Image (cartoon, helix red, strand yellow):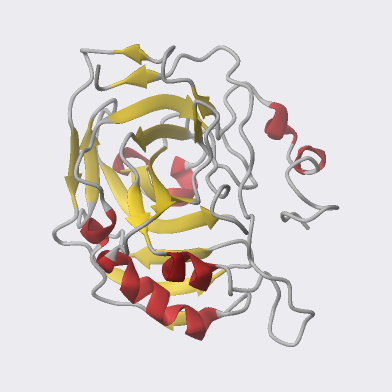
Length: 257
């Protein structure tokens, strides 16, 4: 099945998921000079005060922190969005080295990692329905650079020892995703896709301009995770990022000049 290795990585995914060569694939390179400032865009509204995290899971590709999305507890609104999008999970993509790991790039620059906060449009009732709609999902993407520690990440880092291998889960309650947000909510936005199979073209991407900083020790802990299950040959979970895809007939819009 799909992964990030030599024989099953991003260049192979199109054989099982032909939409991999579609017209609105993600990630993309964000050319900051050709993105268009759009004054019709509203400020984002990030309402995470009542977020209820449940669990953390190693799914063999990344790790996901899952939320209770059965009520409007943590929602994204505004910006380019019409309606209310509920937080269902977040996860990261990261590199084997500090100079790679992000999915989106900015003027071809790669960051050490990228955080995806995944939200679905409540008009569609559940996540599985939402992914089948062109406006089903809103993903808030946040770059990570290596520098000072991010205190709000540490609880995640702490628990990774409990989910080293594929299929392991752990209780992960009372985590506050606000502690992963940078100061500014200035963003770029474009229509795109999931960055992993099934690569569905259901995402309004909102990529924040300002990265967060995490420490060398924090990223190193991500790199100790395993793609494999317990008792299978150890393969470190690193470089779990899809490279930039062609923009095709899309314009990236900026909320800021």
